[PDB]
Amino acid sequence: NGIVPDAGHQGPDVSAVNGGTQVINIVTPNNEGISHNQYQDFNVGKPGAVFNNALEAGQSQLAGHLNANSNLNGQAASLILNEVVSRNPSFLLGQAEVFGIAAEAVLSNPNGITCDGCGFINTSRSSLVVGNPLFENGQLKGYSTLNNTNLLSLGKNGLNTTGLLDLIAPRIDSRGKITAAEISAFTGQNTFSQHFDILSSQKPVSALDSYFFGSMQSGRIRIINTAEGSGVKLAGHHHHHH
Amino acid sequence: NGIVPDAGHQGPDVSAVNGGTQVINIVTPNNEGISHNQYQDFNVGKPGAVFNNALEAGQSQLAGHLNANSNLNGQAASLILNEVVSRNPSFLLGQAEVFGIAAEAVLSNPNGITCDGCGFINTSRSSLVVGNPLFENGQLKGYSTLNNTNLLSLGKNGLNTTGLLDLIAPRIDSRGKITAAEISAFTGQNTFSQHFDILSSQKPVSALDSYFFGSMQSGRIRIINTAEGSGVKLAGHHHHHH
């Protein structure tokens, strides 16, 4: 019951295997190739969650045998955008798998995202955005972390993916092992393009320091904190107030 | 007496103000704009060191009034390459200033480099290379950290520069605040171009993990560890053996 779709036209169908692994029959992709899914709640438990991007029945890693997603009509999604539209933060405590055609995946939740033993399967690029998507004339234009001080937290059990990983938030607090083909961590109050080019940056009211403890196992690591007055702190397992 | 030039044709003239701040009259730049200085020892103490890249007398920050460097004939260096050719590691315990025309600066020492409260003044780009420069037909071709397991250590008093910073070594162990316009840390056993493009990478005999504790205050941070079996560990103030 961790994932609760919005009642409107962008809410996908969600069902759970024996109360466990959640399967999301994502909405039909639009002309941009984006399946834009909106949620009142988005949380993944230990048993994980599957985005059904399959045109034929088959074998998912987390859920076993699944039928095709009948919301797709001949064309799978290129980008699976999951947007939390409520005030509820997200907790990711297990794996998220794209079943079927490999895609990019984005979770946006301006209220905060916590990962702890989460990961992304069959994703070419996975992005966790503590912010909102920006739409203009019905097209995705990018993302915004403006006027937001909430946290992308990564816990001691870490985050694993074979694909590219973007960590996009006002601030990050990571305490575990991050594994990805490449890690990009862009922090501060910013607007971004769809590709996470930084388009603009605000000066925050107070410091937005990010903290990293643990390890990073990746081909490339890039970190950019655009907040004035702020930095990137390489922490031990606690950061006590001074 | 921390800096001891080689006796040959690339050894600069070195003198100390009252036994304190060391002033290096760097050798004449070659047709590539490189002043290629070779040393039996290169160490900077608390009072700092000055590379004299000045065509006229003037005011250095660390040493006060200095005469022009008569080794330059009308043309200042573009790149000040400082190569330790002995087995002695380098310790940088104070600031290093380019007096006169802003230049790029490189210290190469395959035996190890330790920074602790060091920094770089009036440098557009400063590179610390635990490795050797590569020359072919008399021209600088790049740098090599191949077949080397030594350490670029950065201590609790940190490293500060207004320019770009490259940290190039088999492994890095940093325990302080690193301040730079941009930080690039490329670790593992590699060959590099003159611009620190990674041209090739070796598989080391044993793990080459790098460790970072402290903080990074920069516009851009990039870290690449090319060593198989190895990672980037975000440490607390100790990393005890497990």
Image (cartoon, coloured by chain):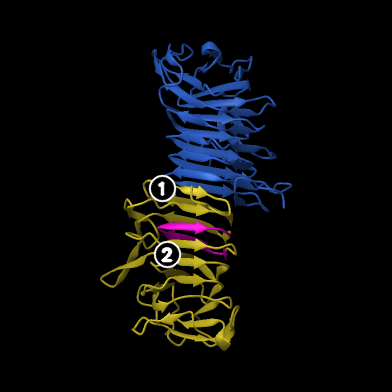
Chain colours: A blue, B yellow
A170, A3: nearer the viewer? A3
B111, A74: nearer the viewer? B111
Q: Quadrant of residue A161?
A: top left
Chain letter behind tag 1 = B
Q: Quadrant of residue B97?
A: bottom right
A82, B160: nearer the viewer? B160
Residue B161 painted magenta: yes
- The residue indicated by pointer 1 is B230
- The residue indicated by pointer 2 is B129
The location of residue A9, given as percent across then percent down, is 60, 15
Mark 2 vs mark 1: same chain?
yes
Q: Nearer the viewer, mark 2 or mark 1?
A: 1
* Residue at 61% across, 28% down: A91
- The amino acid at mark 2 is Val
- The amino acid at mark 1 is Ser
Element under disc 1: loop
The location of residue B47, given as percent across then percent down, is 58, 78
Q: CA distance from mark 2 to mark 1?
A: 19 Å
Residue B137 falls left or right of residue A157: left
Total label count? 2
* Relative to A31, residue A174 above or below: below
* Relative to B165, residue A112 above or below: above
Q: Which label number is shown at residue A139?
A: none
Which portion, as a residue range, is magenta? B159-176
